[PDB]
Length: 48
Length: 48
Image (tube, rainbow over all chains, first blue to last red; front, side, top):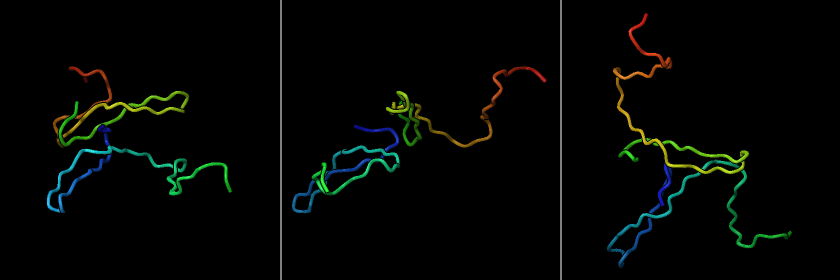
């Protein structure tokens, strides 16, 4: 749902790249920090 | 409640500075002007 003072993103659909219809999607707000970090590799565990 | 084209502020709660949970609060929008002015002193009246 909506988050106060936060960015949002839209998902849209195309019919042969001729119709564009958006949908309210992904309200996201964020604080900056060094603790959280996105990792591309899906596997995460006790490994070397 | 929300005000169109206006800033908003969040109130949050902390459990021993370990959990942060915000609440949609104080939608405020404003025009600039010289009439209204915030005064720190609570007492306001006919005084010198």
